[PDB]
Amino acid sequence: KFYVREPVNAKPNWLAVGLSVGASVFMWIYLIQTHNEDVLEYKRRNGL
Amino acid sequence: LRYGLLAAILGDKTTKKLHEYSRVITVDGNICSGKNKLAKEIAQQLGMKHYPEAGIQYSSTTTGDGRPLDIEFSGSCSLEKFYDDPKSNDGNSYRLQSWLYASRLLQYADALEHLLSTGQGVVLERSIYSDFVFLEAMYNQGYIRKQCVDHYNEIKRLTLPEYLPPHAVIYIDVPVPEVQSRIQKKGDPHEMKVTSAYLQDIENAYKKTFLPKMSEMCEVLVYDSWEAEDPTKVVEDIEYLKYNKGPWLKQDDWTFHYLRMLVQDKTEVLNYTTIPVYLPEITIGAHQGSRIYNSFRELPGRKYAPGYNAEVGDKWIWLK
Amino acid sequence: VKRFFESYHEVPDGTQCHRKTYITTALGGICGIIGSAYSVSLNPADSTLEAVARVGRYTFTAAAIGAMFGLTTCVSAQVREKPDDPLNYFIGGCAGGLTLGARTHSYGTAAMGCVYMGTAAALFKIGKLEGWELFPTPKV
Amino acid sequence: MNNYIFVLSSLFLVGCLGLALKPSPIYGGLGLIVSGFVGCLMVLGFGGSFLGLMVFLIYLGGMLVVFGYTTAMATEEYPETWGSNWLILGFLVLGVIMEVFLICVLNYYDEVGVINLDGLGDWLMYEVDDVGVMLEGGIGVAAMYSCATWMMVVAGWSLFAGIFIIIEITR
Amino acid sequence: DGPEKNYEKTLAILQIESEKAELRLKEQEVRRLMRARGDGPWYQFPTPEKEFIDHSPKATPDN
Amino acid sequence: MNPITLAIIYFTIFLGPVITMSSTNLMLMWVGLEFSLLAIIPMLINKKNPRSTEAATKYFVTQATASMIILLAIVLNYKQLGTWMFQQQTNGLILNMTLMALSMKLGLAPFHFWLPEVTQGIPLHMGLILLTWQKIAPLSILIQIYPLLNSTIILMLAITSIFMGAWGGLNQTQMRKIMAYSSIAHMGWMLAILPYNPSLTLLNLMIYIILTAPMFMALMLNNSMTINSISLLWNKTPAMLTMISLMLLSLGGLPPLTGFLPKWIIITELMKNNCLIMATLMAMMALLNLFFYTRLIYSTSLTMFPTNNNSKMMTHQTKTKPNLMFSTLAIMSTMTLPLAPQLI
Amino acid sequence: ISAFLKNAWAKEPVLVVSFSVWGLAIIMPMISPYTKYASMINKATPYNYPVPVRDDGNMPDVPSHPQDPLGPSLDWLKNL
Amino acid sequence: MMNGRPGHEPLKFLPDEARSLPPPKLNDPRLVYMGLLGYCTGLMDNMLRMRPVMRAGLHRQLLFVTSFVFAGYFYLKRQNYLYAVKDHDMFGYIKLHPEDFPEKEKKTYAEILEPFHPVR
Amino acid sequence: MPSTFFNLTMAFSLSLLGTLMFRSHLMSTLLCLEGMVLSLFIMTSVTSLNSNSMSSMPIPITILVFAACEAAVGLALLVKVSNTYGTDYVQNLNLLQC
């Protein structure tokens, strides 16, 4: 509206955003599961 | 997607879009040669896009708000001041000439980008190729210094070779006495002080350099004043031109792609115009440049990038 | 053979002056010839006689520095009763620096070279006493 | 025959000496042709066959292209031969005599070592399978189609990429 | 808190910073010995591989 | 270049080094070297200007000579030990020649005169490859033979290159040549610590790459190639100045920045091995590097240099060139010392 | 593409023949009963000596005499 | 130095042997510093591209911080494994060779005649 | 074998020496490189034939292939420098001094 050349980044790329947020939440879930598994295995292999 | 190697592979081939009227015509002539009317009419009849002549405000008009900015941001060079005092000891003349050359370069890049993208043709009013006439005329009259001539030629050497020349040039020849008559009639208070010697130097530069140089590669047509009217005649000539001469013939998809990549990035286009050759006329001091830059980077809409200015009316920033 | 150069330390300083002077002169000459070969291979000279003059000048200058260094170091160690005192190598290196300044026709080189070369020689002597090792082999 | 191989190696050395002295590229190509022939003969005398012939073939082709290039680019109004330049001539003779004297010196200092002119030709071949059949170097080379396919892959890729590289260098 | 906290914490500091030192010097000694004698897990430089030897009956008996 | 040439050439440049570092056979390591050599040249001569052609020729001649010397080393090792890998029993001259020829390939002094010229001639986006990706293979070849190298030769080359790079950096005004000389100095450190503990040689290689790539992309941003030209960033692109300063200082090797970690750890190892004189001299002479980086910092970030009238249109126009990798590498190179223990 | 193939057949027959022969060179080896026999024949050819193996008394298949029925038989090669 | 350690398995990030070590605590200072680095990198990207430094690109910033922490966790785990391996080999070798690392007996301070240098 | 290897090593040494010291024409330098290639191939060939190692005879051919590829690249570079300067003289290759 203000700009003559249509701003390249006029509206968010919903695709790129959804991918970024999904990757972030997946990464956090995977990391938490892995940490829990590592704790359990350390206890298992070292007799608690 | 930004035009890149990926898009080129997947399609977007320029030769796929080029057509008969996809050309780069340049209308040229002395001051008040009636260039603008003929340019608009050729563009309209041939279905191409007309680019008004680049002014001191071209970049500002074509970017951001599209509103003319202040002169301090837009070059601090005044055509009216040039005419009032052409030998002013503040070096306005060569500042104006360099700014106009750079703006013509930007306009040429935009027109070439448009041609290579949409496939439509472009009509232009003078261009970087024809711009040296004004500098030569200033030097001959004695308004600018030989070092400034050197600087301009250097920048042209760095910039000009990259871009393809226009397909056809259409030069309107009008003698200096009638040029003066037309200028008097136009009646611009500051323009009326242009000297016959200056006009004749522009004409001499034109005829004795530009047309011989352009005819080597482009297709050059010359129309006198009486022929210039009735543009339909000029449109007919353009229609029945055959371009067997020029660098354009040897291009192909990949050369067009590299030219497109160069033009698309306006930074690379104007990079060499800012070569750090320390010539007092163009050189700015640190304090003045900093003041101008800080003032510019808080204008409405020019503080952040185009898409991220919340003041002007951009939103979704927290996601963009 | 490297025996000739390693013979420098057969007997502490102040003794076998002539032999030690010969050894240092030879070492200086070798360094000068190497430097001259580099300086001719790069930055060539107009005439081949110019090139050979250059090699002669470099070689003789370096040999002179080495000879003066050895002579002064041995003379100091001999006249004074301290055989292994690094101040001797310092005085010898200063003598070498002064000789370099004379050869180059400049007092500033005399002074700078005295300080730097004397410090280098003194540190060399200190290293030889204290057992320092340049270019060691991996011990970890 | 006793001195066969040593003579061939010395001739190879002389051809290489000429090439190093670097006359005009035409004489360089001629010298390298002679050297390639002598090297092929040495390989042949060492029980080889296919390898020597292959070197000779490939080198003939290479020097053909090289000569074609020299006539076009590496040319002078007065090409200099080995004998034309007195320094080249003198150092050619000097190199020949120097190699002779160096041979003598090494023989004297090490009566048996790098060179054994006495006892020369007594160690050319070490072992041979007297009653064998499949012992020909072509078999070993053809192994690239079975046991060393990695060699073939890398070499073929090298030539393939060479095509594109050459075209784009000469664009 | 009182003097005990500082005094006994300082004792712990000294314990840790003396054990670390002894272990660092011990690292120097062990690496020196392993490098010089090749008898340990570290500094075991490679040698060619036996697996790719060919033991099949050859075409000449005396191989 | 058409897409198929781009694919093949870039793929071969990537292949060569991978072959070198994944080959157990000396001839195959040599094959990797040749792959890199052949494939880089068309990228170098892509511009087809008079300077570009000469730079490509210099590169070609030097690298071909180095490859032949290495091949001689390989062939003689074959003649001796009937194998294609260097063993403890291998003749000392063979290893000396290998180190010498790989030094020529790497650009180390006194075989260093070729690198500055080629870097000056070639464009920045290929200068990055030349000064980063093309060093991995030769240094890998050395690291695979580290226990057998010669301490005297290696230390001599390393100190020579430190001195030479430091001295050469001062005189040059050109950024391309400055980065070439910086490359020489850092490689000098890498080879200095190679014979003693190659893990730190690899650490230095990583940090040098991670610091040079950001700087080269910074130069690419405005095609800056001179002190005067880079002086105009306060006008053309103010934002980058802070990180450019930090990155130049890190490459120089000030303590708080990461650049310290390579030099500090390498000095520590050398001292452990009793290499006091060489360690002292190298540390001392590594300060001319800080000097000729501080001059750049003065020119760009701390002082504002004269600008031109036409930079106003550069201001007007938009910019979309800086990558994500720039930010990632720059921060992770100039703000990572507190994680140093994990690095070594 | 019938039109382009038909034109190629007449205006550039050489390339048509070359591509067709290359295609056949790849196709036929997969489609042919006899392909398996090449490697068997090359294995049948006895370049080196057949080394006898010491009889530990529990080797039941390898023969004791060359003319014994046990062991590989080149009847398949004889009547390929 | 550790490349030739017996049992070395080539190009394995975390060998199975590493599961026996206590895994990193996920609020470790090292991982927190990693998150801080990621956040700063996001802010730097904004500033370079001329964006609202802290407002814009929140998805980008979140990805940066999470990626830094994710990489940091595993890299830290591998480093812990490597240092633990070094200590294991250390102490095993020392135990094997008691002769080359004898245990020093220390005299008390009473019996040690430390020279005294007056500071006059 | 011993005398042959000595002479071949000397030949390679001389060709390397010739390459290291130029003499105006770049083509001659390329030829000297090519001669070193010849000598190295001969060394490998004789070593393999002497040892009866038929598994290493695939390697001299690889040497030839890669040396040919680099020689072709060299010739192309010669073509380009000639187009630039009119000759192949190495003196003209001095722009980058500045």
Image (spheres, grey):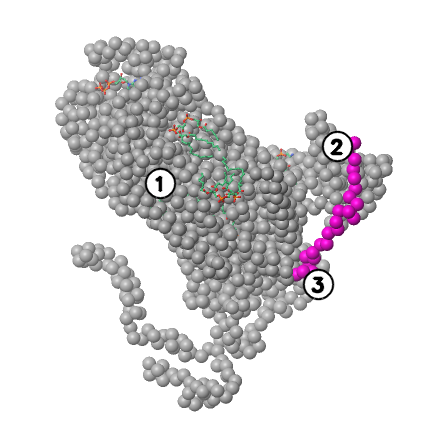
Q: Are marks 2 and 1 in contact (CB under 8 Å)?
A: no
Residue at the spot of label 1: H60
Q: Is residue B266 left or right of residue I75?
A: left
The chain carrying label 2 is: C
In terms of image quadrants, where is residue B116?
top left
Mark 2: which amino acid? Cys
**Residues indicated by labels 2 and 1 sit on the same polypeptide chain:** no
Nearer to us: label 1 or label 3: 1
In terms of image quadrants, where is residue B265?
top left
Image position, residue G31 (x, y; %):
28, 71
Nearer to us: label 2 or label 1: 1
Q: Nearer the viewer, residue I2 or F5?
A: F5
Residue at the spot of label 2: C94
Residue at the spot of label 3: D111
Residue occupying image coordinates x 52% and y 47% = F343
- Which residue sits furthest front? E2
For label 1, the SS is helix
Query: Is B259 inside the magenta-drawn segment?
Result: no
Mark 1: which amino acid? Arg
Mark seen at residue H36: none
The chain carrying label 3 is: D
The chain carrying label 1 is: H
Q: Which residues are magenta?
A: H97-120
Mark 3: which amino acid? Glu
Give the mark count: 3
Q: Is residue B293 visible?
A: yes
- Mark 2 surroundings within 10 Å by alpha-carbon count, few (fewer than 14), some (14 through 19), many (20 or more): many
